[PDB]
Image (cartoon, rainbow over all chains, first blue to last red; front, side, top):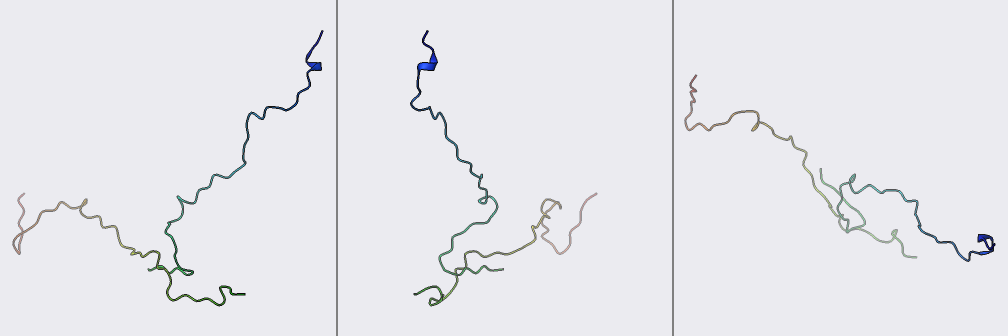
Length: 44
Length: 44
């Protein structure tokens, strides 16, 4: 009458891992260009 | 301790230039046909 009571479990199966991260949306919000100087200046 | 307080900028990066202008929609509003005389006279 051996049951699972006699079966020690060394390690669990992780199965899955998840990171709690924000969906980042700014690419669709801000006009984008790169700056190549410490100061930028736009023309109106 | 050289920091941004010692450095200077010759000219800024323009990055972008704009012009706010009216979207001109008349082409889709008025039937258009060129005249080759100082006076036009349409037929009803």
